[PDB]
Length: 32
Length: 32
Length: 31
Ligand SMILES: *C(=O)c1ccc(NC(C)=O)cc1
Ligand SMILES: *C(=O)c1ccc(NC(C)=O)cc1
Ligand SMILES: *C(=O)c1ccc(NC(C)=O)cc1
Ligand SMILES: *C(=O)c1ccc(NC(C)=O)cc1
View 1: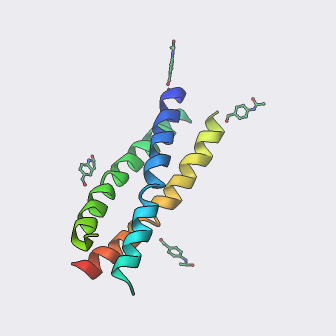
View 2 (view 1 turned 90 degrees about the horizontal axis):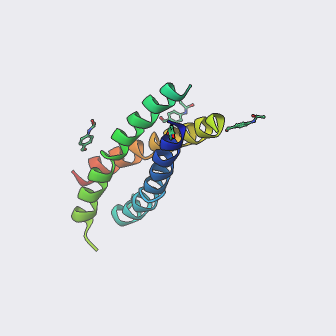
């Protein structure tokens, strides 16, 4: 169970990094 | 401890799915 | 190993919170 969780967490980390970059680019495109 | 973590990771996987979908939609609307 | 996972999961939760806020703002401006 812990090994499987470790792999799920690593996958999530890669996706969240990404979303952060994508969100930062969209914020620039839309502007303020 | 591991069961509790599993629940948390499941909840995160759901939230990231979504964000991915929302971010794909916004990217299509902004273009580029 | 479990404590290392717990730290990683806490970190992700704070990051997803956020992304949700930022995305909610973007959705409102573009919608
Ligand atoms: C949990 O991810 C887990 C638990 C057991 C094993 N392997 C054994 C039982 O041979 C792998 C991973
Ligand atoms: C799409 O946003 C999407 C679709 C299915 C799920 N499933 C979870 C919430 O059980 C999440 C997000
Ligand atoms: C897991 O994150 C983990 C496992 C073992 C230890 N340390 C002790 C001494 O067993 C720390 C962290
Ligand atoms: C977002 O959910 C968030 C982050 C920081 C704060 N700080 C205030 C309330 O002290 C509120 C909400």
